[PDB]
Image (cartoon, coloured by chain):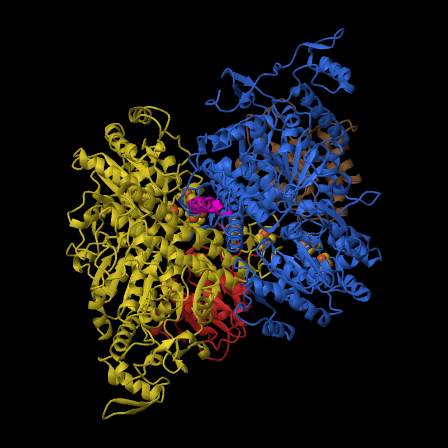
Chain colours: A yellow, B blue, C red, D brown
Amino acid sequence: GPMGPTPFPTAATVRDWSFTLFDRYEPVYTPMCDQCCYCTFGPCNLEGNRRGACGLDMKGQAAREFFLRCITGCACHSAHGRHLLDHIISIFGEDMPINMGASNVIAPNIQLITGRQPKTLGDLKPIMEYVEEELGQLLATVHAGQEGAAIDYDNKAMLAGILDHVGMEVSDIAQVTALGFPKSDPEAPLVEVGMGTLDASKPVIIAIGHNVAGVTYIMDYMEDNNLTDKMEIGGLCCTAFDMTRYKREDRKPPYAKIVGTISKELKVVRSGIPDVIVIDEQCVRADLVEEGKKLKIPVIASNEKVMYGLPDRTNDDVDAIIEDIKTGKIPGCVMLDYEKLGELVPRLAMEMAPLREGISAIPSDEEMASLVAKCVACGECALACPEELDIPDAIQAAKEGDFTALDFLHDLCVGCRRCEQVCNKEIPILSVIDKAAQKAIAEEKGLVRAGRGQVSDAEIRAEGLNLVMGTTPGVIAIIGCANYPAGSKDVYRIAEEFLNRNYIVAVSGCSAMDIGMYKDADGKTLYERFPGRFERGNILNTGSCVSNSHISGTCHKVAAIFAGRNLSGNLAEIADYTLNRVGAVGLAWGAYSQKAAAIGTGCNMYGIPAVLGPHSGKYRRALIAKTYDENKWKVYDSRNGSELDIPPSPEFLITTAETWQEACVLLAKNCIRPSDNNMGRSIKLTHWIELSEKYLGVLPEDWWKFVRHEADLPLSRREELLKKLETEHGWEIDWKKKKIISGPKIKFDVSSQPTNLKRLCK
Amino acid sequence: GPMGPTPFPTAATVRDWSFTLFDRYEPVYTPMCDQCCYCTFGPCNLEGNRRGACGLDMKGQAAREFFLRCITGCACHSAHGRHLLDHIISIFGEDMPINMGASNVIAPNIQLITGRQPKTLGDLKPIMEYVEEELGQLLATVHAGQEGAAIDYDNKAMLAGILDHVGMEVSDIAQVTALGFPKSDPEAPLVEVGMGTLDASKPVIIAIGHNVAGVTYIMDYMEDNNLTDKMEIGGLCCTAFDMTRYKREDRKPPYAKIVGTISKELKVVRSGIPDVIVIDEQCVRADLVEEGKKLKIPVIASNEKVMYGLPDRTNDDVDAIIEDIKTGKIPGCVMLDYEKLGELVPRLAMEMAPLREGISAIPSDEEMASLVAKCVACGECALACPEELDIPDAIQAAKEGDFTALDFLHDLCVGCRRCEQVCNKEIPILSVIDKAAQKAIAEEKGLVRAGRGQVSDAEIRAEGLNLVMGTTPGVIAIIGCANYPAGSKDVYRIAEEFLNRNYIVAVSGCSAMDIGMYKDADGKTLYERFPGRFERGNILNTGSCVSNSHISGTCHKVAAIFAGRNLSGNLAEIADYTLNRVGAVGLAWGAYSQKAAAIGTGCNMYGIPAVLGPHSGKYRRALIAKTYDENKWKVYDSRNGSELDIPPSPEFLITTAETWQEACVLLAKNCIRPSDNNMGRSIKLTHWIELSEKYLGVLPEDWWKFVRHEADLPLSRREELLKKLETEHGWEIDWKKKKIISGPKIKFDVSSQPTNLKRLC
Amino acid sequence: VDTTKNTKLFTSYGVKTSKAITTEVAAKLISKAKRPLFVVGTGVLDPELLDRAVKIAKAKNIPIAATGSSMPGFVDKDVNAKYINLHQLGFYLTDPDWPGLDGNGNYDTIILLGHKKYYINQVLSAVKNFSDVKSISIDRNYIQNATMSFGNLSKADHIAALDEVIDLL
Amino acid sequence: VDTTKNTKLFTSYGVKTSKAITTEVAAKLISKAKRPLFVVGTGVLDPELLDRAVKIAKAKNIPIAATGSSMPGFVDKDVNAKYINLHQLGFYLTDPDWPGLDGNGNYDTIILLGHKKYYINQVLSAVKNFSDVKSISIDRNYIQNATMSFGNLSKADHIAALDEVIDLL
Ligand code: SF4
Ligand code: SF4
Ligand code: SF4
Ligand code: SF4
Ligand code: SF4
Ligand code: SF4
Ligand code: SF4
């Protein structure tokens, strides 16, 4: 029916909104290099904001690099979605209706961007097509001499981010509708997570990747032959969530297990636990064969994206492949036929379990003593460590029978092996750390909730009242990868702190795995302490990486439920509404991948601020606003069209934080919105002040910038803060009524409607 | 009809063919950078083939970088094709029959790859769709942890290259069947090209880029308003060739002019000649706004890919935009409305011509005497020069009154002003060089034949015998950009030398317009001297590099029209035929862009070896064969299925050469195929030995490997070569009746058929 | 105690590199700063590092930007310290019009102590490429993107160097 | 003449840079080499560089590999110069099973002269990162990818350094 101005958008159509965002949130470029390696006219030295042979300055180069990362992430999501959709339509038919959950808008991102309302599975076919076409255009911008300004690369990156969100939504909708995933279930079944959950007394299959097509066939073969009680299947990365959501809408406990994030990927292979490894698409270490052939661990590729230089045995007989892998020259094969793979992997694991027994890279106690005695403290390993761990100090401590420093370093290490390749003594430091933390690994057991899907249109209404009556301080979306600066406990600490204050915490991806890994002193995890509903003090795990499209979609639904705004082709309107009214902040503590960059950029284009880990400064682009400049904090009143002041929150669209206390303070502060009433503003100020005092020893210096009314102040210390306002700031206050009569620079008016667009003013 | 075994190929469908190719031609990785910087786990130092935090080694990283370049070029060509097809369909509909000339295989690359034979302009719509899909499935591989083998990356890069030749094919097909281009015309009109071919007392419109979509509107506005004589329209890069070919099926000479390649861009801006500049999509300098604003040159962007951060004034009135630009309130504008742009550009040029008279960046003699004396010879400019020119020496010579050093430097300089940013004396070195070379810039005139399009069926049928048998010594496809190492005359010299030797020379892109800039004593270019039919001794121009596919398509026609092979879905068999029996070689002496890399990779998948300039060594991957291994030169027989030995030619699929003499020797040597008869091998050996003795100064050290019979040698030197074979290699040759009793390694057989596929024997 | 010895890196940001200075040069540069800003990180919470940082800041009355969660260390102390994000500080330092923490104007030279390499290097890239604010690194890691920096040092060597710099301020 | 004073570069491949060496060090390395190869490019057609290269080759009977168009400069010079493509030579030097130009085997160290900086650097990247062949660049430029290299010099200083090397061999 009614359509907005931007259906099927391009770089020109979303230029106005992106430019409006960049006028307030200026881009900050932190180049990862002083040179350009792109074309034979180079490499060009752009240091000091100089120009290349093509006239491109270093700011433009950084913008182009970030744009390339965003489009690579978008391409990954869209290609995974396209392959999943094609397989699903081939197997289940093109007329299958979309069954996502109890909702009014089943595809909020698709409706928001394209303007269409898909009903069946085939309705998703054109949308994917559009995305891929646009991808080509965007990819054409990576060519040399294809853009001169950095702002035009930032706008194209924003377009790439929103297209990425569309692709993730398409993929998740297809997979959930087809493979019987949980449909917005607040009581999703719990699944074990950790390296100490795989019983080494049974054959072990380990699936690494992000797809689920072949994993479903493997599980079907296991179930049909009743091998589920004697063979253990584990998942690394998002395929663990995808396999633990398979047919789990009935809440039956799943036999599949979750091993961990990318960090564990090599470590498990080092332990000899896996008996067969299958690799699907992405987040797969490019040296699994190198460290697996040493332990006689077969590695099987299953997708054309990743063939790992292996022989292609697709058109063959399973028995011959089994015999060659068992006693032969090939450490694996590429098996692109899904039925053949689902039949081959279980039999191969069964026949390899009794033959690879007693093989692991963990050194003996005497072997580890000799290894720790071999070091000379040359400092190369600490120089090559991505996390800058103090390896030589730990080795020096362990030289005298003190194996606890390596035990501490085990959690901080990411298992990247970069320290081993610079050691002239050939000391396997990763295996040394694993040997020192063997007992801790054996103790690693946790529980996580399976992917519920999207948030239903009933929980949003149930939580809107709590958000407007000042009982829900905001929404925190803990997502991203697992390249943490100081171990996997930081996400757990942040989630626990925000759940203790009755926030709405939504988790997905590797962060959910690394949060559900720390049991409490009572032997409980956060998912068991707090239910999986969309309500205050509750934590819900949406699912795999492609489930993040739901979280952003949730924001869109808030615009489409309480305000009644049209979603079809209304990117600018809904983005403005989310930026001005909805209090939701994303947190990507360990993001490394280009997919994380695409997700963060797409969230920024929807108006959702994000705080990332200290490593994310390597992404070369952030979006920060100048607090001091008062002329960049003005909007229009959608009733008068006049200029209206707003508090300086959110003060960034994407930023980085070093420690988790700083992240907690930033997340608490950035939940504030200009349109907040007295109760919401009061509760947000309360929590922000409390967190600042607890984690910084001081209370914020800009708190007074968020006090429009005497009801804006916290309840506990109202008089203590009013006295400070009168004394430190000189405001005029009445003491009998405890009322601020003068001093605020913005009079409270709940009916005011902030807008960044002049085209929607009376 | 009868369809081959690879319908709509993917990574796995062409994996076997790529592996077969790389079994003979190993990939040589020459990485440009010792670190990987893709994800935040890095920067990962990969020096010494060490693996990164994700397990990728340095060879894998180099392969990934080359694959990224290839897919970038392929996506650029495919996006150009998609935009052109959409815009053309929005005017002429979607049921317009395709007419590329007189032939039956209208789309060779499309039929070879997708097995489809489109006949209407809308029938190309699905093809692009397929390509777009594959593009995504390749770009996802750039993500960290999506592939861990350099060989698989190379296979995917070759697939991207072929999907880049398909995109170029569709682009050229649409733009030729719609806009009225020459239709395989062997008598295309001559076109004035050069710096001095443009006037200066008239308004000037300079079109930079690759999209002839707004240039068409400008040209119609100028022709229907009788402005073809009152102003000048010049073009740079391939948009010049496309603009010239526009509406030129009537063979009348065009009024549009060609200024030069990309290396001339800033130069033109610094000359003050242009009165307006319109930038479309590709090969556009990123600092035109700054220099144009310094020289008060309006800049208009008419595309979504290139916007420059200029205001979007598509919905604004033309008069208001013209007034704002004239009064200097904005440095330029963005206009996506072609109808508005075609009226705005000429009017803006006409109004701005009498407003910037006497405005230029060329220094006066006294200023070029002061700036030259300002230098203190610190050597930073020579360090920062991509072409490694002795700028301080030239400036020192200028301090003595001799300005010939800078005049000689002018041709070698690609005009990138990279020097001017490192000079602490703030000397406009490019401007100084242009001032010292003004006397030659004034003479920069020449003629180039416009793009013919494709090759007609009659020419292919006539030349198939001479090509497969070898009567024509070979085909040289001079393609690529203008990032030359030692000036733009090397390509002209190579083309002239090979045209004098009865070779077929096909040109396209910037090299086509750079060859015709040099004249002989009579003052005529190579295009005027030699005709433009697909015959020995003639030189033909295909135009823009989107027409480059035609050259590759030409080879496919030879494999299909003559031998009767089936094109549909038969990439492996056709590529095998071209590698085994067709004598063709490509030359990219100045390749710099990702499009050139994609084109080269696609050509290498088709079995066409390529020689590139030294700068192409920064492309991070070549394909070279081991000449000292006899196990890499074994094939099978199509009649018996038994092993067969072949001469080690070509010794590479892509490589680089330091100088143009070495390039000539390589092109001469790599045109020899195992299937040539005695006459073809004799002619090829004659040319190779003559070129080697003329340029390298010594007779080749492996010519005796390419001899199987007594008729395989040149007749004028047959006795001398018999003596040379007898005294050194100790062969048995009968002196009474000239015949080789014994000594060779491969025995002659006219009916022998070499194949690299065991499934075809 | 010689700091300009181990100028060793794992990866390089380009050709331009930091200067490895001695204790005397660092003391002279700190004492000659027109308007210094002691940018400190969460890694200064080590008691020796915290004491040395407080002594350095109070010796020359240098205002402190306690980036990260380093504010609780300075609450009990006397040095004028304010909290600010390191990324936000890097964005602000590239603006000549920034009033600063005191509102008296933008700063000239920033002293860095107690930071992670991959973070401070990323911020210093923008700071050193899009501004003219000088950076002096007195950390035990060799920072490439700083204008001047110490070399790779042991913890005892770093403590000794900081003590010598204190005695030479 | 001092050859280890100017090592300025425009760009850098990475942390591992070439060692700056003197004339005496280069002479000692060339004398100690067991099976050296003299890889000359088309830039040894200079009237002076050709004489220096011929003297160097005749001093130690080093076989010459001429790349590009330098072969005519050795047609009648009484040396052992043979033609080979530089890219092909760089690929073959990474294969230990190469018979070599002479026919005995591969080589241990190669001396570079008369090359273009970018081309020789790109060709040497593969040799440095994928083989164990040492590189001695005696050219006028500072090649980073070489094992040992002369620093940046003027033409007169380049000639003086080459003459000093010859007189010390
Ligand atoms: S960004 Fe990476 S690849 Fe590009 S020049 Fe810098 S180090 Fe090299
Ligand atoms: S793209 Fe531009 S900056 Fe990069 S290498 Fe090429 S000319 Fe230099
Ligand atoms: S690299 Fe090896 S020898 Fe050097 S400090 Fe580390 S563990 Fe010890
Ligand atoms: S494997 Fe662990 S300890 Fe070694 S460099 Fe990588 S993160 Fe550091
Ligand atoms: S992609 Fe791999 S090699 Fe490159 S920076 Fe990331 S972890 Fe390191
Ligand atoms: S950079 Fe400038 S001062 Fe230095 S040598 Fe070149 S022209 Fe002379
Ligand atoms: S403008 Fe010319 S002389 Fe200057 S650096 Fe570029 S190519 Fe060299």
Compared with A704, C3 (above or below) is above
Magenta: main secondary structure? helix
**Residue B636 picture location, percent across and down:** 52, 19
Residue in the foreground of this view, choosing between B3 and B480: B3
Query: In front here: C73 or D11?
Result: D11
Is B606 left or right of A737, judged from the image as shown?
right
x, y percent for residue B496: 75, 38
Asked if residue B125 lies in the magenta stretch, the reply is: yes
Q: In which image quadrant can residue B291 be found?
A: bottom right
Residue appearing at x 58%, y 32% in the figure: B557
Image point 35% across, 43% down: which residue?
Answer: A430
Q: Which residues lie in the magenta part? A: B121-139
* Rendering coords of residue A634 (x, y %): 42, 78
Left or right of A499? Residue C63 is: right
Spot occupied by residue C84 in the image (x, y as percentages of width and height): 40, 70
Q: Is residue B89 above or below residue B358?
A: above
Front-most of A437 and A346? A346
Is residue A328 something one can see in this rendering?
A: yes
Q: Is residue A507 magenta?
A: no
